[PDB]
């Protein structure tokens, strides 16, 4: 029952800070992603709900 599996609404600064926390800047985000990739993250985490663990899998 780890808290990182609790889904929530990641919008605005919450989503930016969550990406810095679980995905980091070095590695995945060192290469710019696509606008469609960013559309899917906002859709799955801001419009819908996603967990920090689910967000980590988007960055592999």
Image (cartoon, rainbow, N blue to C red):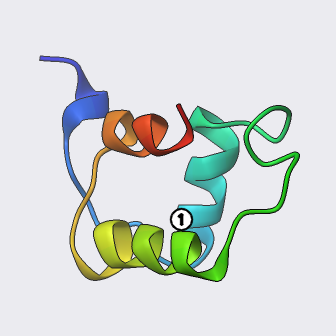
Picture mark count: 1
Residue positioned 32% across, 41% down in the render: 54
Going 86% across and 33% down the picture, which residue do you hit?
26
User: Crowdedness of circle 1 by 10 Å Cα count: few (<14), some, many (20+)?
Assistant: few
Q: Is residue 20 above or below residue 1?
A: below
x then y, percent, for residue 39: 49, 81
Q: Is residue 22 left or right of residue 54?
A: right
Q: Nearer the viewer, residue 54 or 12?
A: 54
Q: Is residue 14 above or below residue 25?
A: below
Residue drawn where x is 35% and y is 33% of the image: 53
At a point 45% along the width and 67% down the height, the residue shown is 41
- Residue 31: x and y in percent read 85, 51
Place of residue 21 in the rendered image (x, y in percent of width and height, measured from the top left): 63, 38
Quadrant hosting residue 28: top right
Residue 4 percent across, percent down from the top left: 31, 31
Q: Nearer the viewer, residue 59 or 52?
A: 59
| Residue with the mark numbered 1 | 14
Q: Nearer the viewer, residue 43 or 32?
A: 32
Q: Is residue 19 above or below residue 5?
A: below
Above or below, 18 relative to 8:
above
The quarter of the rendered structure image containing the N terminus is: top left
Q: Nearer the viewer, residue 8 or 35?
A: 35
Left or right: residue 35 versus residue 56 is right
Is residue 18 found left or right of 2 in the rendered image? Answer: right
* In the image, farthest residue toward the left: 1
Label 1's element?
Answer: helix
């Amino acid at each position: 029952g780890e808290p990182r599996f609790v889904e929530q609404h990641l919008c605005g600064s919450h989503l930016v800070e969550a990406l810095y926390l679980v995905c980091g800047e070095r590695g995945f985000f060192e290469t710019p992603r696509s606008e469609d990739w960013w559309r899917g993250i906002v859709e799955q985490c801001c419009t819908s709900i996603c967990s920090l663990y689910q967000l980590e899998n988007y960055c592999n």
